[PDB]
Image (cartoon, rainbow over all chains, first blue to last red; front, side, top):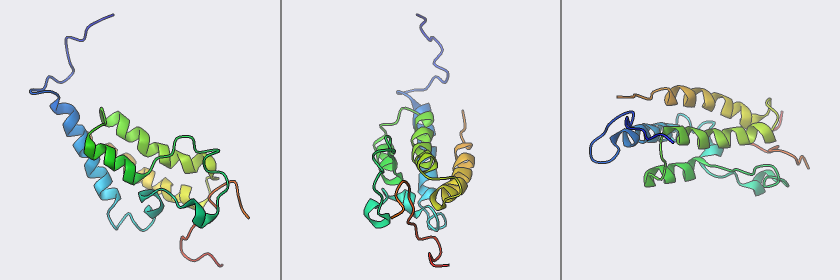
Length: 128
Length: 16
């Protein structure tokens, strides 16, 4: 066991670093909810209405469902421990359509371009 | 019915 005497980024109060990174993540979802992205990301904003498509096996495949509404909620509550976590659950729902739907299919194609803007948006992580 | 995936989206116009 080794105690980290260097906390990477020494912050006053409690943990300024984590807050600044998560706030950037809020900036991301705020944009991903913007009407410009709503043209194609509309199915990801809210949990898919399974009745509408007439699926018969979402829970049988999708063991870790996530949606852009719920994820933002937890972010607003700041239950997220850092940026690594935020990126994980966003890619959760994106990869959900990927494994359950063939890569040439609609949702995964829409997610494909979301993944693009998302990847760049998450690349905007300052350290100091 | 096309089960086993999300075969039922509204992209442009599912017709042709």
